[PDB]
Image (spheres, helix red, strand yellow):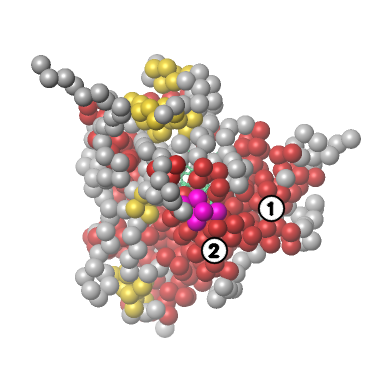
Amino acid sequence: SLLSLPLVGSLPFLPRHGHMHNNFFKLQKKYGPIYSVRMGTKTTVIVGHHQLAKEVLIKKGKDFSGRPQMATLDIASNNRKGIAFADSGAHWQLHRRLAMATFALFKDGDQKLEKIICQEISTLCDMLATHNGQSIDISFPVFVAVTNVISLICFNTSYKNGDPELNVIQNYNEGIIDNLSKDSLVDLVPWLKIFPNKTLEKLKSHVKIRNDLLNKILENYKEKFRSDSITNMLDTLMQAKMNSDNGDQDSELLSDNHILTTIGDIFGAGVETTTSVVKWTLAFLLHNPQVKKKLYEEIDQNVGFSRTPTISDRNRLLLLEATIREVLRLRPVAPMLIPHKANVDSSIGEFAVDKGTEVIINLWALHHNEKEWHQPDQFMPERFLNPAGTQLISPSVSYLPFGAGPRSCIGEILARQELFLIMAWLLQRFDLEVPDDGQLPSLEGIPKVVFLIDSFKVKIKVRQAWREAQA
Ligand code: HEM
Ligand SMILES: C[C@]12CC[C@H](O)CC1=CC[C@@H]1[C@@H]2CC[C@]2(C)C(n3cnc4ccccc43)=CC[C@@H]12
């Protein structure tokens, strides 16, 4: 006969305890695969089942193609310009399309995507080779390689080794990622509006520096540019721009700031995602020597040492394809994609969703659904193979590492080639070992905009059999 306390507020688990994406997924046992939390005025819906997710992303994909406002995203996107963090509409549709259309200047020519990639991988391998017998962090050499790839695709410039501008990019990259969100993007409680903090101030200084740096390349490129040379991304965007004076409906959408941010998004997305996945891949091979050995045998049997690996090679290095697929399952780069938002009054699984409501797909939930996968916690590349190991299969519909629909990733083709190639070249040539202290990388992860792995070292060695075939 004692009374319930008045309740001003309720949350279903602790903030800043454990990973968000896993917290949400544990909740699916009591509350089912779809539920909502209310923050002040803002309502957020979380979706943990492939069918409900495919509804959000494909079937009613335009209804949910929105992105919410966040004070952090604002600053990194110079107030919702660019692609990723721009809302649905005029500006987004064009720049998305333009960047997608650029991926075609590399279908097959002097600058075939596979060539640009390989030349930068050749360099990575030569730099790696001098560290023969040593334990190292590979984060930066890889970062360089994929920075040059993304540079070549953007500007047709790359950097010489030792170019200081690389270390500057690295610094502001680490900064922006660090301050963009504490953990995940999805912030149950908005602490940054509650307690005095320096977070937005920090982030403006890093982005100011990124902006300064891309502004230099932009002005200076105005000289090189010619309307009868479309070889790279800035040319796609400037060609579209002077295609906006007739007697101009697309000129407002392509100011220098709009162009800045778009390149920024591609420059960033291009570097940080794939470096993380490479780091994640080595980490998994270090914990799984049996898979590593079977990767050596496969590359030996099928490529051998007579030449260097090729895009065509994905048709015979099947276990390598399956490993990548399984790193993308088990540690998805974006475990909750990026937040969607209802453009209009709509529904999911026939529940009402109001215009402007935040919608998150829990990719991690999909990728660990125990009804959809055998032993979802486990690193099992075999799961993407038929039992005899002679062909790739799709064991589950509950698999969307690159998302789906209108907000899907535009960099999948680039990402996929890059990752297979980097891993292929690295295996052909290097023994990759636990460094001389028995320290194995933690596989827990660090959720930010990208799902990162704690930094770690590998003992790098030139392969017996690679030196053999050098006589
Ligand atoms: C391992 C590599 C990658 C993975 C797993 C990945 C996955 C994703 C996912 C899951 C999304 C968001 C889907 C959503 O919000 O519903 C996304 C968005 C995006 N990705 Fe990637 N991505 C990768 C690499 C790349 C690369 C290399 C690029 C560079 C060209 C890139 C460019 C973008 C852009 C611009 C968006 C925003 C799309 C939009 O809002 O319209 N991504 N990606
Ligand atoms: C913050 C950062 C990376 C560091 C840079 O200094 C600033 C920057 C620019 C745009 C961001 C990018 C990281 C990844 C983002 C968010 C991204 N993106 C593209 N594919 C992704 C897959 C998973 C997570 C993010 C993904 C699209 C635009 C990208």
Residue 60 image offset from top left, x and y in percent = 49, 23
Q: Is the C-beta separation of discs 2 and 1 under 8 Å? A: no
* Circle 1 crowding by C-alpha within 10 Å: few under 14, some 14–19, many from 20: many
Mark 2 beta carbon near ligand 2 (under 8 Å): yes
Of residues 195 and 216, the one drawn nearer to the viewer in this rendering = 195
Q: Is residue 249 above or below residue 345?
A: below
* Lateral position of residue 200 relative to residue 371, left or right: right
Pinpoint residue 435: horizontal percent, then vertical percent: 27, 72
Q: Is residue 38 above or below residue 110?
A: above
**Residue that badge 1 annotates:** 234
**Residue visible at 44% across and 58% down?**
275
Q: Could one spot residue 92 in this view of the protein?
A: yes
Label 1 is placed on what type of residue?
Leu
Drawn side of residue 371 relative to residue 404, left or right = left
Does the magenta stretch mainly form a helix, a strand or a loop? Answer: helix
Q: Position of residue 236 (x, y in %)?
A: 70, 48
Amino acid type, residue under disc 2 in the picture: Ile
Residue at the limit of the structure toward the right, as seen here: 247
Where residue 208 appears, as percent x and y from the top left, is 59, 57
- Magenta range is 199-204
Q: Which residue is mark 2?
A: 169
Instruction: Tell me if residue 149 comes above or below residue 263 in the rendering.
Output: below
Placement of 228 over or under 434, stated as above or below? above
